[PDB]
Amino acid sequence: AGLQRTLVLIKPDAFERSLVAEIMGRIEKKNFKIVSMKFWSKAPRNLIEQHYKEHSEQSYFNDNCDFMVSGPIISIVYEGTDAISKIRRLQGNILTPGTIRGDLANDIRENLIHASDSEDSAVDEISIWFPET
Amino acid sequence: GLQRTLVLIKPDAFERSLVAEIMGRIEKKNFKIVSMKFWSKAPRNLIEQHYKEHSEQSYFNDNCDFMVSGPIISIVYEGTDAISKIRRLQGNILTPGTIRGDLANDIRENLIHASDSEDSAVDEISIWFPET
Amino acid sequence: GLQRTLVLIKPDAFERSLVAEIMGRIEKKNFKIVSMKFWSKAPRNLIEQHYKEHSEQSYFNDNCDFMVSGPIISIVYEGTDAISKIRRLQGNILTPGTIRGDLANDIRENLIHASDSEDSAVDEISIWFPET
Amino acid sequence: GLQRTLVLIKPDAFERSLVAEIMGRIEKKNFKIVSMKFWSKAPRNLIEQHYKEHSEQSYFNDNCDFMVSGPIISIVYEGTDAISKIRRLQGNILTPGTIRGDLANDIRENLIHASDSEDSAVDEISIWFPET
Amino acid sequence: AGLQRTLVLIKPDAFERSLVAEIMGRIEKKNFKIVSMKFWSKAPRNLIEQHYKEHSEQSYFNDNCDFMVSGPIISIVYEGTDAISKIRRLQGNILTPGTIRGDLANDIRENLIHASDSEDSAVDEISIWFPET
Amino acid sequence: GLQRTLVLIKPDAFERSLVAEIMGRIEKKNFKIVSMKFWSKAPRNLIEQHYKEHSEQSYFNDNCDFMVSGPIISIVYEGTDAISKIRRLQGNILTPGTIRGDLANDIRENLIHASDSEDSAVDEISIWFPET
Ligand SMILES: Cc1cn([C@H]2C[C@H](O)[C@@H](COP(=O)(O)OP(=O)(O)O)O2)c(=O)[nH]c1=O
Ligand SMILES: Cc1cn([C@H]2C[C@H](O)[C@@H](COP(=O)(O)OP(=O)(O)O)O2)c(=O)[nH]c1=O
Ligand SMILES: Cc1cn([C@H]2C[C@H](O)[C@@H](COP(=O)(O)OP(=O)(O)O)O2)c(=O)[nH]c1=O
Ligand SMILES: Cc1cn([C@H]2C[C@H](O)[C@@H](COP(=O)(O)OP(=O)(O)O)O2)c(=O)[nH]c1=O
Ligand SMILES: Cc1cn([C@H]2C[C@H](O)[C@@H](COP(=O)(O)OP(=O)(O)O)O2)c(=O)[nH]c1=O
Ligand SMILES: Cc1cn([C@H]2C[C@H](O)[C@@H](COP(=O)(O)OP(=O)(O)O)O2)c(=O)[nH]c1=O
Ligand SMILES: [Mg+2]
Ligand SMILES: [Mg+2]
Ligand SMILES: [Mg+2]
Ligand SMILES: [Mg+2]
Ligand SMILES: [Mg+2]
Ligand SMILES: [Mg+2]
């Protein structure tokens, strides 16, 4: 059919603010299924830098890494019809009410969640967090 | 500009236990229930009539099969700008914040139907609530 | 031990926009809707019959007046241990966690009615859904 | 980045018991309460100053009467880009996902007020919290 | 009728954990109305000690005061039928799911909310937080 | 005061999409996730060890098959009095306010498992997280 898989990361601020179930629930209610899930008490900076390698040239690149390893994170692989962009739309941004970041986040860096933005990004990101491909 | 529109809560809503969730979103936008019917299984006739305008489409038959594969609730809602607002509340599976935007993810199994114009509203209401 | 019980959603539920909230609590406990009717204003006859056992009480007349001062929904729910469980779900205005425990605060305006025994269930269902 | 904006929870919010619901959406977006006051009935001169930029509109008088028809809560929220962000949260009755889009459906009884600019924010805050 | 007024205090841990609306919403949904409300960025230890004067002899008395002034608090006066005990039952304790403390709290001291436990306590507590009686 | 207990989110939880709902109730009670694992299908020997104290019961085999009929999540929660508190949160299908009381209605498909003692907690955690 139109089956797809995408990679989501629940960020440290999510645990800090007790919004983990809240975020996962929004994705769950949109009818997406967990295919793989891993809890990281503290992720290796290595994986983070690979995950954000495309951003290695930006000014915010190192502070973002500091943050991404400042607390726990959960890497999840969701599956569903048109999953990559639907979950991306669900993630939204801090300016659009109705989405996860729009309702719960308010910072350029501490935005609670990451979602693959394309097929190439997904395949690559999933490989990073679930090497046992 | 007070109006009345027709809403159908689809089988997938019962399957996934989202009936109250959906009705609650409409109720909280302050629209009232004027009439309502519960159908364990809707008569295929009614369904075909409801989607008459689609009889020529390729998705017609399967859609009917689905619309009868479970219970459905027919509801007539009243309120200011009801048709337009409930339609907007229904949304689509792309934009978060709406019923379909937050809970649906299929082009066919989209939980709810809402009239899209004054004309279809009057017609749809007559189909499910002939007693008028 | 599959059963069917009758539930009435009272006027105060429509007044306070808690209809979906209440139906959602029952739906989430996994009980299904077997039949349902919406009444803009319930016929006083039905109400008097429903509360027959109370005809001698001092609160009878006022209760009837209230039960007809707004819309009400009659619902027949099915499920394992339905009568007992939905009754427990209905609770009372003292114990938090139940429908009345979290949302009601009056001895008369308590949002919902649920049969309390196998006998009253069969009788109550016959009153609102004679077509049996 | 830090800003402070003034929000007013309107009479209809108390009537419909949506006060916690509204304040909750702002709290979940991570904004903090700096100041807050509950008015069982706000002094009319305060309301008129608050809407002074509207003093020549046809709806001015009626709106002020509505704002004085019940309690209201004035709150000073602090947070990054607070003015713009809380303004978008409020939205309008045509935008699902926002406060007015999900819970309001009237041109006047629209549950909430939020400053629309830095000047209006500064002016409005001094109106409800002159003690600074 | 059976009209009553009671005094509720939203505690510092409530703001810390962003549970203020949540708590007030549970009381709001049970059909109780706010008659007076005051926001304290930091309450004067004086009022706290008066509020808990009956506990002045307990070991936990000073730490509880330290906490009660460690952050903001909101004093509210609710009104409704049988308000004092109904709101008291709503408050519940950390061992009873279904109540505010039962669902959201988990400590002997940081328990999110205070509710008058009797008519005498209410009248006295209300006087403490709303002297303009 | 600090304890650590083992929780299992059962297959029915994924089937009924109640995973976030269940985990949310534990998260809102202030318990923290220490360890967590998702199993699309848990190895049967793990389930049998987990319920080894039940190995002689008539329901043993059927329960194990149910526990292997879908994904499950094993979590180690840490918090003050975690074992007892999370146990009460789980409750039973007769107790409104708890997880099973609000969402479950079966003797076997009861959505969640939580250690009932310090020894069982210690044993259970080593079964799902032997890497310690
Ligand atoms: C733009 C930006 C991003 N970041 C971090 C957090 C962002 O989620 C991450 C990726 O940036 P980006 O791709 O711009 O946003 P999204 O995550 O919405 O695609 O980099 C900052 O820390 N500061 C910034 O200014
Ligand atoms: C377009 C389309 C519709 N349908 C069914 C389900 C749609 O809800 C129903 C009506 O279609 P439509 O009128 O295009 O959308 P809405 O219901 O948003 O106005 O027809 C399909 O089964 N497959 C399709 O490709
Ligand atoms: C006891 C009582 C009941 N009533 C009305 C509303 C009650 O829901 C209805 C039925 O009473 P009852 O059977 O005692 O309670 P339940 O509905 O919990 O079984 O009668 C009053 O109006 N005043 C009263 O004092
Ligand atoms: C435009 C308009 C506003 N009002 C009232 C309610 C509006 O919230 C208030 C302020 O007007 P306005 O600034 O247009 O709306 P907002 O509050 O979205 O900026 O005036 C009316 O009563 N009638 C009207 O036609
Ligand atoms: C019993 C106790 C109370 N306290 C503080 C917080 C309690 O909410 C407050 C009042 O105690 P108490 O009357 O026992 O509980 P409640 O507040 O449920 O009536 O004193 C402690 O700090 N430690 C304790 O051991
Ligand atoms: C008692 C019982 C349990 N079970 C299954 C589901 C129970 O959750 C599991 C463990 O039994 P038990 O310890 O009695 O329940 P809990 O999980 O509340 O401690 O065994 C059955 O399938 N049939 C039964 O009759
Ligand atoms: Mg990106
Ligand atoms: Mg259409
Ligand atoms: Mg009775
Ligand atoms: Mg304005
Ligand atoms: Mg006390
Ligand atoms: Mg057990």
Image (cartoon, coloured by chain):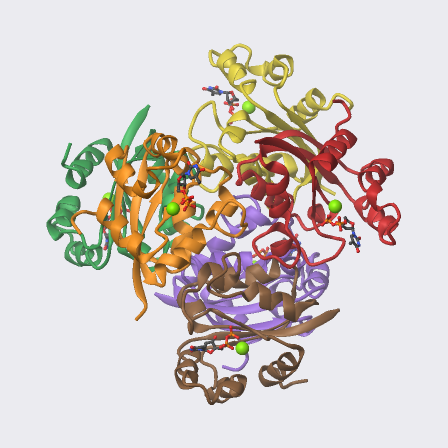
Chain colours: A orange, B brown, C purple, D red, E yellow, F green
- Tag count in the figure? 0
Question: What residue do we see at 43% from left, 50% from top?
Answer: A91
User: Which part of the image, by quadrant, shows the N terminus of chain A?
Assistant: bottom left
Residue C109 in percent (x, y) is at 65, 54
Q: Is residue B86 left or right of residue F27?
A: right
The reply to whether residue A34 is visible in this rendering is no
Residue A81 in percent (x, y) is at 35, 65
Question: What residue do we see at 49% from left, 51% from top?
Answer: A99
Residue E64 in percent (x, y) is at 51, 17
Q: Is residue B48 left or right of residue F103?
A: right
Q: Is residue A109 left or right of residue F84?
A: right
Which residue occupies the foreground of this view, C87 or F22? F22
Question: What residue do we see at 17% from left, 58% from top?
Answer: F65
Q: Is residue C36 left or right of residue A8?
A: right
User: Which quadrant of the view contains residue E95?
Assistant: top left
Residue F49 in percent (x, y) is at 13, 45
The reply to whether residue A133 is visible in this rendering is yes
Farthest residue in the front direction?
A: A57
Question: Measured along the vertical axis of the image, is residue D96 above or below residue F27?
Answer: below
Which residue occupies the foreground of this view, C107 or D56? D56
Question: Measured along the vertical axis of the image, is residue E58 above or below residue F104?
Answer: above
Q: Quadrant of ligand 11?
A: top right
